[PDB]
Length: 236
Image (cartoon, rainbow, N blue to C red; front, side):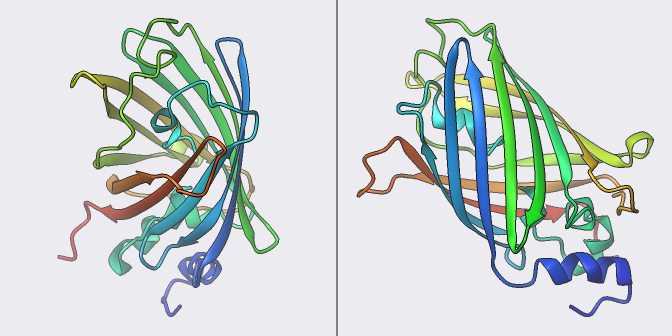
């Protein structure tokens, strides 16, 4: 709304109100081709996302929780005193590319590339995923992950070399037996547009995710409620 920085204004004006979201993923893990479609809504005011995802090719070949991070950080709530650090909104509506390599300890990797942009009044997340070197008897392809997710903090750093950001963070996936599977994430984001973006000072995003199921849905699916809040810069 009312921010003294016109560049902040431009970003926030796009994300006042509830914004419909479409997610498309095409994936290939160890010779298993699959497609995920998701729909829902984001509200950056509260840093809230509600998404339903379906596997449109049948049974998802990997555990759903392994895809949470891959399946829109522009819906993060940035407090008022941190809005000048919100790279994700500044890049809109033209969008940004989000690339990751995800290493599952003692197992294979995912390589993802995503474009996040507005198509009309809809925020679209278009993802390609390639997973290689997974063990058939491992926790991933053997479906030994629990269906739940753990809160955590992701550190965001500017990359002034590429007018973007980078992040490296670990996800810990609970395994059936009470162990954990670590998933080491490396991420970089770069704008699609040539125009200026807001390059953040170092800060973190605090993420909460709750996974559930739609009792009426017979297709392989995941319902995701996610809260993301920016923090780590104090109103001094």
